[PDB]
Amino acid sequence: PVYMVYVSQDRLTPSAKHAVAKAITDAHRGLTGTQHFLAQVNFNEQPAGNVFLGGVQQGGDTIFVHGLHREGRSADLKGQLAQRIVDDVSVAAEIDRKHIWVYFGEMPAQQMVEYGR
Amino acid sequence: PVYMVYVSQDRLTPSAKHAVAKAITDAHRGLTGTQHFLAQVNFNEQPAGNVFLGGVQQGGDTIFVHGLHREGRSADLKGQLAQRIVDDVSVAAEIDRKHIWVYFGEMPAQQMVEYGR
Amino acid sequence: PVYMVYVSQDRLTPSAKHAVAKAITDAHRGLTGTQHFLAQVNFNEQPAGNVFLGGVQQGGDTIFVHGLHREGRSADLKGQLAQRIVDDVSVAAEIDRKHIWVYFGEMPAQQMVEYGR
């Protein structure tokens, strides 16, 4: 799959970015059984002040993980994976769980290409 | 929900960004009844020249609103919400309606986490 | 439709960006019959080092094409369009096919607005 991770520039050091990527990647491999190399984590950073919750401009602590998955997994599994990402990312980024949002989108495998194949 | 808003850097002043966020947030709360704090607006800015319509490189006026919603709302409602966003954002950003694109994506509530819960 | 294209800053020159946009746009028009002007290509660039495959930090060669489409097209067609994008983008960006990922997301036409309509 592909995990788009939206964070504020400078909030995560290159070291934290790696730890967050590993956390997400390990959770996915661990719970779905999909090979590690098949998981992409793409960080999209924006200047502080581009996030609004309830119309209020936030700091740089929000982290929105948008996971693009292959269809076919149970609701219970996706639920566990979503929670696992929250707990592990919170630890990896040393950021309070309340700052983490996670949304999973699905698509049939037939319209998904990874590594050009 | 989470509204990813793609704009060109500098096109929206911090003041306009707030107005655009409030517009979108008010429309969602107003039409769906979902609490204000449950609506996130995430602005993703890119340098002018990263947008192409029909293969032609555009200026910095395009605004693409990609709304990530919870499944379960009628087509009529989503239709009204989409239009409401077009009218209100056009007013908030003082930008002609023709520059506004709006796409809604849906996901079951079970694979959606907000505020770590 | 709207094609979000995630690349690393400076990897694509403005000339390559245009060629990549045309490639994608031509493939979509050619295979679906949807008018050229109805296809938006939105490049989202990030500094080198924001991409991780299998938890490993990559260079600036990855290109993730996330196509947001209107529902209703066959699996075979979406399959051909996905492949066509891989071949043509690889040529347009003079980048090896292994660096190209392509994911298609779908939504009913009723919750899709282009050019404010």
Image (cartoon, coloured by chain):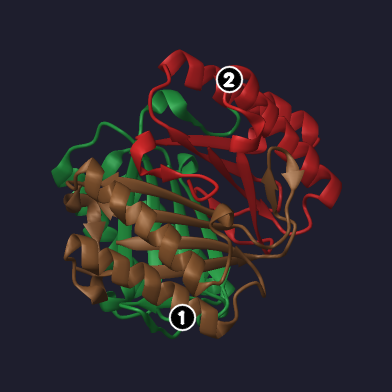
Chain colours: A brown, B red, C green
The quarter of the image holding the N terminus of chain C is top left
Residue B6 x %, y %: 61, 50
Residue lying furthest left:
C76
The residue lying at 60 percent from left, 81 percent from top is A13
Tell me if A86 is positioned left or right of C10 in this view: left
Question: Where is B13 relative to B34, above or below?
Answer: below
Q: In which quarter of the view is residue C35 placed?
A: top left
The residue wearing badge 2 is B33
Report helix, strand or loop for mark 1: helix
Give the x, y percent position of residue A106.
29, 46
Tell me the residue at 46%/66% (across/down).
Answer: A89
Where's residue A98, x and y in %?
Answer: 57, 53
Question: Is B25 in front, or is C9?
Answer: B25
Q: CA distance from mark 1 to mark 2?
A: 39 Å
**Image x and y of residue A23, in percent:** 38, 72
Tell me the number on the disc at residue C36.
none
Image position of B17 (left or right of A76) = right
The residue shown at (24%, 56%) is A112
Q: Quadrant of residue C34?
A: top left
Q: Residue at x 54, y 42 (%)?
A: B2
The residue at which mark 1 appears reads as A18
Q: Amino acid at mark 1?
A: His
Q: Secondary structure at mark 2?
A: loop
Q: Nearer the viewer, residue A77 or B64?
A: A77
Q: Amino acid at mark 2?
A: Gly
Residue C83 can be seen, yes or no:
yes
Q: Residue B89: which quarter of the image?
A: top right
Q: Chain of mark 1?
A: A
Considering depth in this image, is B108 or C31 the residue closer to the camera? B108
B43 versus B2 height, above or below = below
Left or right: A105 as drawn, with respect to C73: right
* Neighbour tally class for label 2: few under 14, some 14-19, many 20 plus, Cα within 10 Å: few
